[PDB]
Image: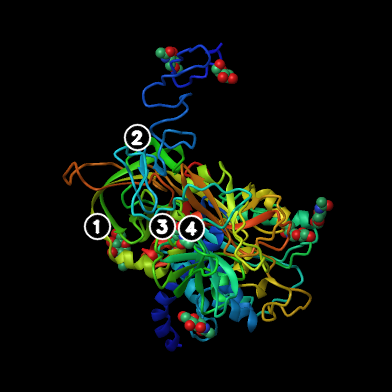
Amino acid sequence: SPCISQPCLHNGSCQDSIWGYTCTCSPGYEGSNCELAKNECHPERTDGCQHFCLPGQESYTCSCAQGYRLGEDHKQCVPHDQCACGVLTSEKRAPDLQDLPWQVKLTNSEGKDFCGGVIIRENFVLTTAKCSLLHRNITVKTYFNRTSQDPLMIKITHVHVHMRYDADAGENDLSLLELEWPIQCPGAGLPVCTPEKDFAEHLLIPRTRGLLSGWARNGTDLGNSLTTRPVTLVEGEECGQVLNVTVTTRTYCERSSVAAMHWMDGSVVTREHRGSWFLTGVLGSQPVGGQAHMVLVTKVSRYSLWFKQIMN
Amino acid sequence: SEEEKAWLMASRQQLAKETSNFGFSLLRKISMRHDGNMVFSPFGMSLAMTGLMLGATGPTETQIKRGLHLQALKPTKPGLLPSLFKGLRETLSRNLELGLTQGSFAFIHKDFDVKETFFNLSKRYFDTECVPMNFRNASQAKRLMNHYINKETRGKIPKLFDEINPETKLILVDYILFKGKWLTPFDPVFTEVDTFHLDKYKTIKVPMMYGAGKFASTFDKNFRCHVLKLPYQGNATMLVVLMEKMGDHLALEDYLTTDLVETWLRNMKTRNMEVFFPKFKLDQKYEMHELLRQMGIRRIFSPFADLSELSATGRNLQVSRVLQRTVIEVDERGTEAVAGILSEITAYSMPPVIKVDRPFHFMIYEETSGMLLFLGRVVNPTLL
Ligand SMILES: *[C@@H]1O[C@H](CO)[C@@H](O)[C@H](O)[C@H]1NC(C)=O
Ligand SMILES: *[C@@H]1O[C@H](CO)[C@@H](O)[C@H](O)[C@H]1NC(C)=O
Ligand SMILES: *[C@@H]1O[C@H](CO)[C@@H](O)[C@H](O)[C@H]1NC(C)=O
Ligand SMILES: *[C@@H]1O[C@H](CO)[C@@H](O)[C@H](O)[C@H]1NC(C)=O
Ligand SMILES: *[C@@H]1O[C@H](CO)[C@@H](O)[C@H](O)[C@H]1NC(C)=O
Ligand SMILES: *[C@@H]1O[C@H](CO)[C@@H](O)[C@H](O)[C@H]1NC(C)=O
């Protein structure tokens, strides 16, 4: 022991400590094993960027999410707006308690709740296209930090339905909802983070669990009981047969073994990374082979441009 | 009639604009099925389908016309095809400067009537020798076809087919191969193995051609991408679309319209610049009918299709398969036997640079007609 594994590749200077080892990789490298490079981006890099990374020529570069700025660190993401998808210091497991700021319900001409949605920005709410289209007087309703008696009501000025949406093909089932007034954050609520494609598909979805926040329908206990649930990626291959469905390149699958019909469509999956939550999926009309434990989500990481174009 | 010709001239352009929009719809349906390298011919695809739209009637024929984004053309009967079938001629005929192996086949069942009408009239337009086959002796049928093609293609396409259902009414193939002569070939002294980011987290090493001098380009500040014109010989051109460093190329596909392409074709500005471009070679076959179904063209691939005009014999005649094989290669010399020579006179050491080291889209159109020959996407220069 211990420098026997030769664990230091790429000219790694093995400093044999007494209980573990250490390395001093050949110039232009890093890591406890030297498997990294200041050249590219590796998912394993712990001391890397807090949010988004860009493989550079010499070293890599760090970008930040909506509402953040980089500290003098050039790697850190100091939140300052303030509207930046940070879940208050609050742990929630078996007791979901409906206390996440970005979740939202949709009502029509009467108190009827028919769909869910997510705050994407102070004045925009994301949801499925199918839902956005079955009523012409949609209103946004949030209970975050509010007496259950009266919720927060906001009228929907205009609904931007994705331009490549085909209901038949069930593809691009997504809409953006323009709020009459901005959400008074962080009090009234708070937008969730929207991730860059590569980041979201290389270190988020494959490498960590997410939780599926929504509501079951059509039923409840005469109230708004937001029920969450851990989920993991299902390899599209298997997912194919298991649901008797063809997985396009803008959808993926999740599973939990809790046999709950997350009927509410605006239900969404999210994953957190270094203390920030990222919208990873939006729950289409997952069907019909249920098999309720496995779910079919719309890959939000793909519609990054569509957001910027519409919301600016 | 001289009446017809007067029309065909104004309809040249409208037809080109429309099958480019048809081409971008196709590209999108394909992009739904995978993220890898992609390449196909919008033009060869419309040309082929249009031939069928001839032998079709009513609901069938009508649906094809709409599906090809050109129900707006309101002509007399077959004139619609001569546009496409004769555009095919002008390209393979007097134009040797480019490519351009191209052709199609209609391997039909050995019992269809095929009157002396749409058989000679269609041969006058399509010029695609139909070939009655023994889809019963499936094993024999495969060999024959692969051979027929292995011939008219000159070994370029070896064995196109793998299987064949015993009950195959009609199969339709279309191939197109291309590699041209650069207007300004790249200096092989300068091509070096360089870094190519297959994506932000994975990268590889690929041969990177280098070229300097005058190029026409433009940067769309809205979607934030570079557009670069690489001129071939024979008035064919290649548009290279390269998103800024952060943004993803897959997003841009949703926004590709003929209007966009031409709006930044006009904002083109020719100037001195350096360009790094990766060698590659895409070869792909698509079962187009499966895709053209998802796009709305369904009836002509289904039992109740009306090919009555083609072959009145009524059992269950219908296009069974449509498949396009297309190949395109890009080194620094092309079809020329020697490559190019770089001489530096601009003169400066600070001209704009443009490295194609991320995935990108490329289009290949004939500057003359504006017709889209090749719609493609290169995510991994190493395979294909
Ligand atoms: C570093 O690795 C190379 C691999 O070729 C090896 O030849 C060399 O001996 C190593 N250098 C040192 C200082 O051990
Ligand atoms: C629709 O929404 C408005 C508020 O914008 C509300 O006053 C009205 O009661 C609703 N009903 C209908 C049917 O429009
Ligand atoms: C509302 O939000 C404020 C600020 O977070 C908090 O102090 C208060 O307790 C919350 N309660 C209600 C019912 O609004
Ligand atoms: C779809 O699922 C059903 C389940 O009974 C199966 O019969 C059918 O073959 C499937 N279609 C496929 C796999 O394309
Ligand atoms: C198929 O039919 C042809 C008819 O010429 C015959 O020569 C050939 O042997 C047959 N193939 C097989 C596998 O028997
Ligand atoms: C054709 O292509 C050549 C390429 O040198 C170009 O100079 C010319 O303007 C184009 N025009 C016509 C009508 O051929």
Q: Mark 3 vs ligand 3: CB under 8 Å?
A: yes
The chain carrying label 1 is B
Q: Nearer the viewer, mark 2 or mark 3?
A: 3
On residue A59, the disc is 2
Question: Badge 3 is on which residue?
Answer: A186
Mark 4 and mark 1 on one chain: no
Sequence-first tag of 4 and 2: 2
Question: Badge 1 is on which residue?
Answer: B270
Q: Amino acid at mark 1?
A: Thr
Q: Amino acid at mark 4?
A: Pro
Q: Nearer the viewer, residue A178 or B137?
A: A178
The chain carrying label 2 is A
Q: Amino acid at mark 2?
A: Ser
| Residue A258 drawn at (x, y percent) | 70, 52
Question: Badge 4 is on which residue?
Answer: A101
Q: Nearer the viewer, mark 4 or mark 2?
A: 4
Q: Is residue A152 left or right of residue B194?
A: right
Sequence-first tag of 2 and 3: 2
Q: Nearer the viewer, mark 4 or mark 1?
A: 4
Sequence-first tag of 3 and 4: 4
Extreme residue toward the left, this view = B347
Q: Nearer the viewer, residue B362 or B331?
A: B362
| Residue B86 drawn at (x, y percent) | 48, 72
- Disc 3, disc 4: CB below 8 Å? yes
